[PDB]
Length: 215
Image (tube, rainbow, N blue to C red; front, side, top):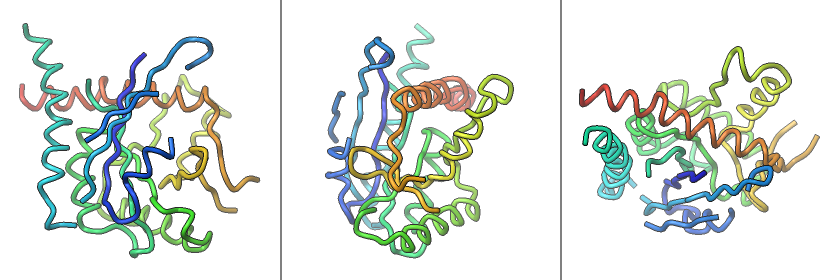
């Protein structure tokens, strides 16, 4: 079971060191069965450095184009948008990127250089990025769940995952919190299940909207 995850975000901190904390492609098991993850990185952008995102937008659209093509005779299931912190909430480029591409790819916001900030600094930045997501109605993957199927306790876990957003993912992968533990290392089973929901979300609805756009 192959999976496509793309890393997008500014040079600022280090978009090149982030892939290591897990254009260039890189490949990396369930409850016995083999699961090969195909992570792909893009160049870091700055509003003036605009010709670097149109090719990401093209790649995404083009992957969805070659499926729709095969259905008439490789697509990205998750976007890890690296946000540079400190700089009060979300930038105009961070905003303009995720509103367009948020309809085509499952964007999940992450925070770069997490270890170079305090807990109070991190709480703040988390609060603001989320405040700018609401204000600009930014279409982010907010862990949608099957109302009847994925029920109770697993719901409580999903409410907690959403809480960790924007993911400050550092060290041995790990996500940082604010309040039992400071670093959260996701159950191998849990990460895979979500990957299956992003794989399914980009096929069941995200490709469906793009298919009913050209048709």
